[PDB]
Amino acid sequence: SLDWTCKHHADLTLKELYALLQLRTEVFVVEQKCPYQEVDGLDLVGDTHHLMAWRDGQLLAYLRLLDPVRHEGQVVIGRVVSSSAARGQGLGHQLMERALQAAERLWLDTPVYLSAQAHLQAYYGRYGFVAVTEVYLEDDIPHIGMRRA
């Protein structure tokens, strides 16, 4: 049981912004030992949205939605993350489900794009995503761009 929220960046509170950057850093930077620029500048521009799932003051799952006019006509889903303590319970499916619904609500009929890790390529194919690029590297981890409908 969680409290889900999908906000436009212009409506974030200092607490929330901090929280979502802290979760993202904890997973993409620390546990994944990747000293890259997590605060990439795409968080507070255009209509970037932020999907968050909260439980008792803790942010357990998050994903970011980048608007289509700023991304050549595709809604971009990224920074998909779930707290290590709340994993294996299907938060991934809840995120993807709400993300697709949010994209639909915000940018109806706009195809969705994401950069998926080379391996979990089938996982997304089940959500209707299909490969659109050759495999490329991210922190030496193979990824592949996929788009849905």
Image (cartoon, rainbow, N blue to C red):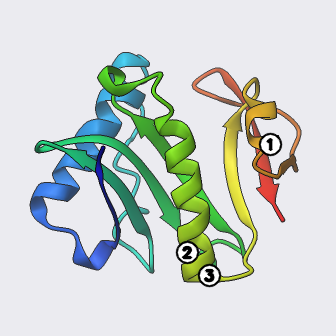
Mark 1 = which residue? 126
Q: Is residue 8 left or right of residue 73?
A: left
Amino acid type at mark 2: Asp
Depth check, mark 3 against mark 1: the one in front is: 1
Identify which residue is drawn at 28% across, 37% down: 23
Q: Secondary structure at mark 2?
A: loop
Find out whether the residues at labels 2 and 3 contact each other: C-beta distance under 8 Å: yes
Identify which residue is drawn at 55% across, 74% down: 67
Q: Quadrant of the N terminus?
A: top left
Q: Residues within 10 Å of mark 1 (few under 14, many from 20)?
A: few
Q: Is residue 121 left or right of residue 30?
A: right
Amino acid type at mark 1: Arg
Mark 2 = which residue? 67
Say whether disc 2 or disc 3 marks the residue closer to the N-terminus: 2
- Work out how far the residue at label 2 is from the one at label 3, CA to CA, in angstroms: 8 Å
Amino acid type at mark 3: Trp
Q: Quadrant of the C terminus?
A: bottom right
Q: Nearer the viewer, residue 115 or 125?
A: 125
Q: Is residue 32 left or right of residue 113?
A: left
